[PDB]
Image (cartoon, rainbow over all chains, first blue to last red; front, side, top):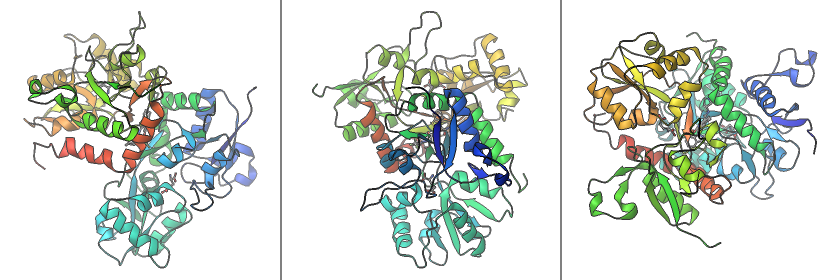
Length: 263
Length: 263
Ligand SMILES: O=C(Cn1nc(C(F)(F)F)c2c1CCCC2)Nc1sc2c(c1C(=O)N[C@@H]1CCNC1)CCCC2
Ligand SMILES: N[C@@H](CCC(=O)O)C(=O)O
Ligand SMILES: N[C@@H](CCC(=O)O)C(=O)O
């Protein structure tokens, strides 16, 4: 029927969506800033809809429980009808593609290694061949699943270690993973997406580093419930924004214009 | 109805599809080798179909004539019903997305600069600010369209030069562009996709080089006629192959295992 205000699910993840310092001063969409806040505005303008940004209730990206088969996170909010679109750093994966629609990618990324500066690790192979430096991933996301399902020798070796490590090497939020790298004196390395790694690398106190090549190559897509009428126009908008250079401009805005660690 | 032999349109473009040295000895799909030959085999296996590789009649990727509105190339072969699927380095673009279906990307690329080794050019900006070194693109493709439609200062400046340059800076095939770089003594630079640039860089006589960062960021997708039943299973196959590491393995096979210029 007639156009309705679109409910957008997203996640507090820097620099994609961040609470403005004075958010209690503010209301609605104005509380938030970042790459995905800007992207949401652009997509909405190019598709002719009004929208409401909402932070996913459980603070998760989206995973399906093996027993209950229930989806959590942003994927859950789409699947169960709580939100109309997810505009966030949501990784395109096979298991998700089967239950939600994805746009063509608006940003590329790969799994990558974050270290505290001076940590004697250059690669995944290096991590896998030692035990003094612990390492882990975010839970309820595509990185954890990557290791869990990998049949590649090095990554299987890493997963075999991570799943049984004590204390737990897994974290609830990216900020938690970063905090642990920073506070563990080089004895913890964090496996996270290159995009987030490269952002943090240019933030004070300038004490972390991305090392080695990416472990995989993929992208984030804008997600809609399977068969939603929003899917087509949203996909065209992403392609138009890409071709206009708008996506590149926004990356510059939120990553390198935000750089606090020099050149 | 019942499963039918799938007609695959593709293009002779190294290392994606190449005629085996002894092709006149061979018949059908066995005449060809390369990344997209291997990908076609994998996609067909994972989707449960039989197929016939065919080289696009006009040797073009696909562009729409401004007057007649007729599509040429591989895109034309899909649009007019001559082929069931395109498995090739076919760039995902807005204008194409509106007339054909694309899988999620199976390979990333960006527009890039090829020079003869020793050419005093480091960037697009460098090319745009001089006239002694000519430069151009392939015709009937996404790179030419990129420059034609760009509102970005440097690229508009480049397009303004390229469209009126004499003699023509445009070429019919990638091999032609490469031949011209190689034979023009540093007085021609070629604008082509990073994937093709990086392949040629590792081929004898080892006299070309990719310089500067990419001008854009995008990907190739597997294409089907709009609404075709093949689209869904093909897209899942691409994601599965990505997640299994098969796409990375095939890239290594055809780019770096094929490297003739040392380390
Ligand atoms: O192909 C990719 C990344 N990418 N994404 C995927 C997957 F979709 F997640 F499966 C895969 C790859 C590569 C390897 C195979 C699987 N990236 C792609 S394709 C593509 C775009 C962009 C992109 O990042 N977006 C650019 C990056 C900079 N500005 C926006 C933009 C529109 C045209 C098609
Ligand atoms: N982008 C990931 C979350 C981050 C991670 O898993 O490292 C996802 O969509 O699940
Ligand atoms: N991949 C391009 C062809 C190569 C180019 O334009 O540089 C296309 O699909 O049109």
